[PDB]
Amino acid sequence: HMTPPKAEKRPYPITTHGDTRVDDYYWLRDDERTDPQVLDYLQAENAFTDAALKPQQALRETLYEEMVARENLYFQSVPYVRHGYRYQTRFEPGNEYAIYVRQPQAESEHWDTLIDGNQRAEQREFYTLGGLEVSPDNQKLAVAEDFLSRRQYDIRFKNLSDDSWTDEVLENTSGSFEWANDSATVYYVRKHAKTLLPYQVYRHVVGTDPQLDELIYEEQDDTFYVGLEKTTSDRFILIHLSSTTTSEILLLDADRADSTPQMFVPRRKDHEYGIDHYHQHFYIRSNKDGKNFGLYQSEQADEAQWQTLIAPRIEVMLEGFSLFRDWLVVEERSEGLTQLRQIHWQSGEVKRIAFDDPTYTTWLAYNPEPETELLRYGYSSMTTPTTLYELNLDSDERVMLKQQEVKNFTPENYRSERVWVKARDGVEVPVSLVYRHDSFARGTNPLMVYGYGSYGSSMDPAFSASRLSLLDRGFVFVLAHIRGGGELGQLWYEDGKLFKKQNTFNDFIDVTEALIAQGYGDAKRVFAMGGSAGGLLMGAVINQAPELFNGIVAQVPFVDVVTTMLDESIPLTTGEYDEWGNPNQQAYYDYILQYSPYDQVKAQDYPHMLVTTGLHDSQVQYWEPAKWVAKLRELKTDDRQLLLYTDMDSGHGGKSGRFKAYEDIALEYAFILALAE
C-alpha cells in the first residue's frame, strides 16, 4: 500500500587503494546535527514505521503489559557488609529511582538513608548514579552523578554526620575514583574535554577547590582506557591502563602522603595483565605465556620473579579471580561452560562448584571483604531465573540469598538444550536453546536466533523474563555462540576478528541451517536479532544468506564499516583497529569490504526487517543504519517490510528508562510475532 520515504541520492566518491566506492547517502552524516534535510529523512522514516506498525498497537499493549506483570516493583537488594556497615538498595513502585540505605553491622532495626535518587533528581532533566562509596572512616560519602545524560560524571562529597554536602564538584570524570586510607584524599579519572576519553588521574582533598587538585598521571595513547582500582589489601590504589590487547598498571601507596605512580610492568603489545595485592604478595592474571591466561604470585613487580600458580592451558580460559583468607577462587571457561574452582592456600585442595543444567552461566559476585569463608556467586540459566548463592568454601554449604522473581511463570513448562554444530570448516560451534514443551512439535516452531560475536564478549546462556513472551507463543529461542565471542576462550575470539571476522557470519548461518535440518524449527519461520556488533552480524548474514531468514531485527547496527574505519573523526574508530583492522592498509580494506554490509547490499530479495538507531551516541552513529535502509530501499527486489525506527528522546534513568526498554522490546516482538502468525 504505502510509499516508503526516498532519501535524495548525492553521489559521493571515496577512493582508497585505487578503488572508488560511490556513496549516494554520505550526506545523512551530520556531526553538527543541524542539517534539516537529514532530520526530515529520519522523521519521515519514523512516521512510515509508525504507519506500517499501527495495526500491531493492541499486540504491543498485550506484550508490554505481560512483560511488566512478570516483575515485582518492590525490590530490595541483598544486603552486604563493608567496613562494619550493612548496605541495601531499595525500589518502591511510587519512586522513579533507587534509595541507598545503610546501618551499622551490629544494628538491625534502624536504617539511615545514604542517598535518595528521587531527591537528587529533583529539578533536573536527567539523573544517573555512576557510583557511590563511603570513605574508610565511614564519615564521608563520594557519589558520581550524571545530570546531563552525556556519561560525564560529577563527583560530590556528603558529610554523613550532619547530612551536609561539601561545596566542590569534580567535573567531567569517568565516575572512577578511589579513597586514600586517610578518608580525606580521593584519586579520580578526568575525561578529555574534546574526545571524552578517560586520560588523566588527579588527587583531590575533600572540601577544597578542585583548582588545587594535583595531576598524578596523563595517558599519552588514547587507545588506552584509564581506570582506578584498590587492592584487596587496601595498601595500593592502581592506575589500570588497558587497550584491547595491552595492559600497564602503576601503583599508588594508599597510606602515605604525596604518593607518585610506581610502574608495575611496562606495556608491551599483546601482554594483557591485571593485578591484586594481598597476604604480602602480588597476584597477577597474565597472558605472558599463553593466550588463555595464567595466574602468578610475586613479591615484586619484576615479571622475572612471578611464580606460576596456574599455568595457561589450551582447553581452559582463566577469566578472573578473587582472594580470601584460606582460598583462591577462579572463574574459568571450559568446553563451552563457565566454571568456578577454589584452591586452598595451604593444602592445595581443589574444589569445583557443581551444577546440573545444560545451558547456564556462573560468575563471581560482589565479595568486598576477604576475611571470610563465604563466597557470593551468581547463577542463571535459560530455565532458572538469576540467583545469588552464598557458599561456605570450607563446609561446601550452599545457601540461596536471592532469586529473580518472575510472576505468571512455571519453570517446568520450558526445556533447554546444548547443541554442538559442526561448522563448514569442521570447527564445533556451541548453541543454547529454550522452548515451551507443551507447544513444541518438531519442524513446526518458529525460531529466533540471537547472536553478537565480537570483542570476545560472550552471549552466555541466562534467564530472560521478556523472552517468555516469545516462548509462550511457540518460539524456540537460540543463542548461537559464534566465533568472535568468548564462549570457547581467547582463541574463539581471535578466530572471529581481524582476518578471521567472516567466521562470525559463517558460524551464525551454519548454526541456523543445522537447527532447521535437525527439526528444531520451521524452515519458513526463522527469525534473527542482534545489536551493535550483533547488527554487523545481521547485516552481513542477510547479504550472504538472504533466503535463510523470514524476518530480522537489527538494533543500532554497525554496517558502514569500511567508510567508518577509514575516518578517525568518528569517536570509536581509533580504538577498533585491533577488532576489524585498519582499512588504511589494502589487506584490511579488502578483507573488511568483503563483509561490510552497507557496501555489499545488492539487487536481491531480502527478509522483512526492522532496523533501529538513536541520536544519543549509541556505539554506532545514527547515520549508518539510516544510509543502509536508504540503500536497501533503492536496491532490494522484494516487497517485504523494511522499517527504520530512530529514537529521538534523550533517555531517562530510573523506572521510566526501564519502561522505555520494555516498550522497545514490545515493538520488536510484535513486529516478529505478526510475521510468524
Image (tube, rainbow, N blue to C red):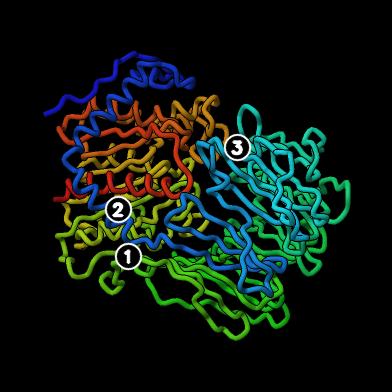
Say which label, 3 or 1, has the lower sequence index: 3
Q: Residue at x 29, y 58 (%)?
A: 477
Are dots 3 and 1 in contact, CB under 8 Å?
no
Q: Which amino acid type is marked by label 1? A: Val
User: Would you name the residue on which mark 1 appears?
Assistant: 419
Q: On the image, numbered disc 2 is attached to which residue?
A: 449
Camera-near label (2 vs 1) is 2
- Which label sits in the foreground, 3 or 2? 3
Q: Amino acid at mark 2?
A: Val
Q: Are marks 3 and 2 in contact (CB under 8 Å)?
A: no
Q: Considering only order in the chain, which callout, 2 or 3, is on the residue closer to the N terminus?
A: 3
Indicate the secondary structure of the residue bearing disc 3: loop
- Callout 1: 10 Å neighbours few (<14), some, many (20+)? some
In the rendering, at what x and y percent does residue 205 appear?
81, 44
Question: What is the number of the mark on residue 152?
Answer: 3
Horizontal and vertical percent position of residue 433: 31, 62
